[PDB]
Image (cartoon, rainbow over all chains, first blue to last red; front, side, top):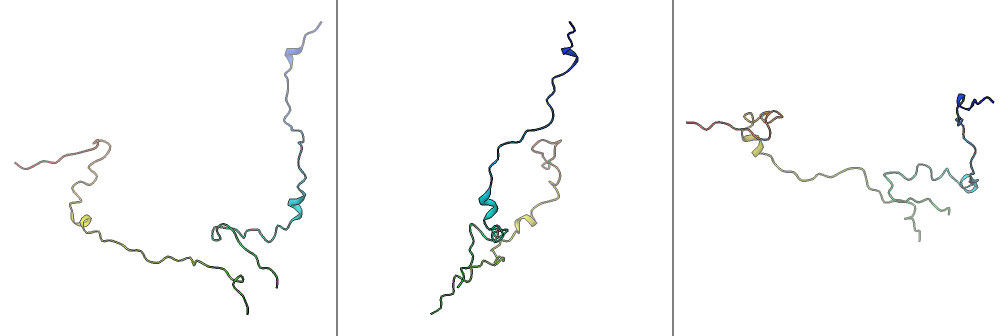
Length: 53
Length: 53
């Protein structure tokens, strides 16, 4: 008839479980290089590229 | 006929023109040294000088 429950604490470990996460195909497969750093504070709202002849 | 104007962009150079300006002659000539440093935290918001007898 030993009652030891007050000798110990109730721990919550410092660890997290994995979440649900979307796949992100479209972001990783469209071209990201052309548009990088091209809109800035000299440019204004938008910006344009040249169609080939 | 050629049409070239989507090749180029409408640029605003980084430079400013001159503005107009105005002269400050009253400030220079009124009395300066007599009221200098006189209104401070020990004084509250006003101070006084003596009329002659």
